[PDB]
Amino acid sequence: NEIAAQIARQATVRPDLSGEGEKEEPFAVVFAAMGITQRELSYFIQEFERTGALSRSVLFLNKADDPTIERILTPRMALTVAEYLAFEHDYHVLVILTDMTNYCEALREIGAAREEIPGRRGYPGYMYTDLATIYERAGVVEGKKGSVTQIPILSMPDD
Amino acid sequence: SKLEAILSQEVEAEIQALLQEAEAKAEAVKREAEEKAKALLQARERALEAQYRAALRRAESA
Image (spheres, each protein chain N blue to C red):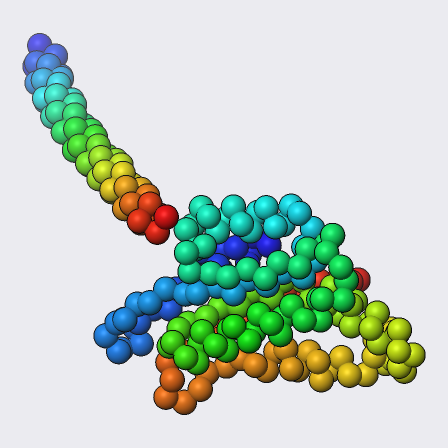
């Protein structure tokens, strides 16, 4: 959380060594949280109000005490807005998708309610396609100076 | 008498060398103190100006 916070508050593209003059626009943070508990939530929002980023950022909070199936909608709903603000307004959107392990547990729950044959360690087969359709809505396009750079935070189970 | 006179002349030369060493040490100490105070005052003034700029930026954002 603190690594993501430091890259949220003090990361900056350097235009001068790239040799293009400058426009030096700061970032725009799409912070989408999937089952962060309360303490991490407190730390992220106080970090953002101390760096003053909440006048240029959006939060899709889906906390731990929230219901457990809307985690499937949260990242796609965030990255829709990310695609939007990148590719219609020439931005430099950075997207923090916190704790994908809760997304994958919710995907496991909806895969096992429908009896579907899982792969390794009880996760269903279409998890590849769904993590693909979360991740690969990102990159840069030709001509349009909008851009999306993602930090998804994983939590490795047995590290 | 000649050897005591030669030793007294050498003692006067050593006293002059000691006074010169004390003067050079005082000069180097004053130079180092001036450099340290200049660097500290510059760092403190730049920190105050940077804190004022960051607080004004956060206040304007608010």
